[PDB]
Length: 260
Ligand SMILES: O[B-]1(O)OCc2ccccc21
Ligand SMILES: OB1OCc2ccccc21
Ligand SMILES: OB1OCc2ccccc21
Ligand SMILES: [Zn+2]
Image (cartoon, rainbow, N blue to C red):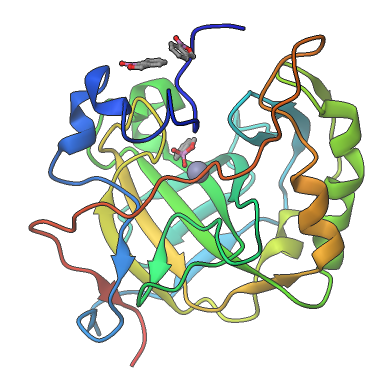
């Protein structure tokens, strides 16, 4: 019932440029990762993902995805190294997923679409908070992880099991004591490039770090994502599926690989 951007024919990615002309900008995300033209950069550092002191707080259905939110008021869960200068603090994670196992990811790999994509969102501590960070060209670092359907991911199950309590837009629930390390693959090999948010306001503030190795989740786990709703409670049901933006033009960018 409310006026909002979304993923429908009438309010989806093809419309967003009218309110957010940066949608047609020079560093938009996601992109297709052409693995054959990405260059290995020996100058890149190992990525340092340090999530041992992470403090999860809450899970929220914001009408576009669900966010698992963290206490970012101290250096507790940080990303550094790789392509990054300085230290970026974890604020939230969320996913993008499809109506069918053959689509759902935002980034693609040689045109391959995965069933879903996880975004671990971090802000550059030099700018003091998330709101100020998104006003900067190096304000955010997003760790992107592909999901394929296969074996269950045990570290995902606590998330799946709470989704029924946040079915509709605006619902939240406690989500303490969640260890986000259980959402990572074994390998930290990655691609990186400069880009943007993949949702309005589409701000060009992101260093993307996209892991090469997908995680596998079960058919049952991703089905439960698809029972969420875009609508509010008491409104007609519109399933939260296909909340992904398609690949955008690479323009004058290079994608760098951390591996040979
Ligand atoms: O993928 B997204 O555009 O969704 C919300 C978000 C927040 C921070 C960085 C990137 C994103
Ligand atoms: O502001 B709007 O939110 C959803 C929608 C659908 C059609 C036309 C306008 C709007
Ligand atoms: O600029 B827009 O064209 C269609 C629409 C729907 C919802 C929100 C914004 C827009
Ligand atoms: Zn995202």
